[PDB]
Image (cartoon, helix red, strand yellow):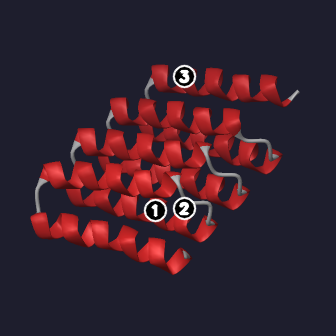
């Protein structure tokens, strides 16, 4: 059932907040991702992605944000629905922005790039390029721009 899985996901967050520790929040990211892996329902997958964003915000640590980005990318790789993939791409930008660190933005470009490689729908590829550009904008650094250009170019090389 869908609402069954969604409730379980929400409860992981609830129970992680009750614990109230950084360790519990990192574990909650992992637990939500594991639930999302063996799920096929798009509403569940989007819900998992949203909850991981909320866990990320609750923690705010560089490592939690890194792990959240990885978890969302993991969910997005095994997803087939384009709406889920585009949501995952936009949420990765939001997670990276919770920190704004050069490292987190770098991870975000890599994550979005990985999603784009697995995708088939050109609409997803367009969104990935769009958000990769925005990530580089958030950074402002020269290397972030060049990582984003190389990432964008590879997606276009795959598109042809």
Residue 132 drawn at (x, y percent): 58, 38
Find numbered disc 1 in the image and state the secondary structure of the residue it sits on.
Answer: helix
Residue at (46, 77) in percent of width and height = 4
What's the mark number on residue 48?
Answer: 1
Residue at (34, 49) in percent of width and height = 30
Report the side of 120 relative to 152 (left or right): right
Front tag of 3 and 2:
2
Instruction: Reply above or below: 48 against 102.
Output: below
Distance from Cα at disc 1 to Cα at disc 3: 28 Å
Name the residue beneath numbered marker 3: 147
Count up the numbered dots. Answer: 3
Distance from Cα at disc 3 to Cα at disc 2: 28 Å
Residue 47 drawn at (x, y percent): 49, 68
Q: Are marks 1 and 2 in contact (CB under 8 Å)?
A: yes
Distance from Cα at disc 1 to Cα at disc 2: 5 Å
Q: Earlier in the sequence, mark 3 or mark 2?
A: 2
Name the residue beneath numbered marker 2: 45
Is any part of residue 140 visible from this angle?
no
Find numbered disc 2 in the image and state the secondary structure of the residue it sits on.
Answer: helix
Report the side of 157 relative to 145 (left or right): right
């Amino acid at each position: 059932d869908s609402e069954e899985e969604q409730e379980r996901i929400r409860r992981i967050l609830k129970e992680a907040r009750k614990s109230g520790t950084e360790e519990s929040l990192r574990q909650a990211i992992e637990d939500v991702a594991q639930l999302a892996k063996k799920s096929q329902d798009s509403e569940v997958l989007e819900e998992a992605i949203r909850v991981i964003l909320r866990i990320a915000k609750e923690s705010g640590s560089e490592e939690a944000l890194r792990q959240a980005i990885r978890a969302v990318a993991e969910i997005a790789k095994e997803a087939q629905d384009s709406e889920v993939l585009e949501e995952a791409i936009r949420v990765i930008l939001r997670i990276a922005k919770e920190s704004g660190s050069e490292e987190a933005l770098r991870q975000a470009i890599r994550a979005v790039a990985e999603i784009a490689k697995e995708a088939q729908d050109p609409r997803v590829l367009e969104e990935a390029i769009r958000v990769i550009r925005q990530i580089a904008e958030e950074s402002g650094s020269e290397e972030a721009r060049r990582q984003a250009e190389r990432a964008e170019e590879e997606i276009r090389r795959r598109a042809q």
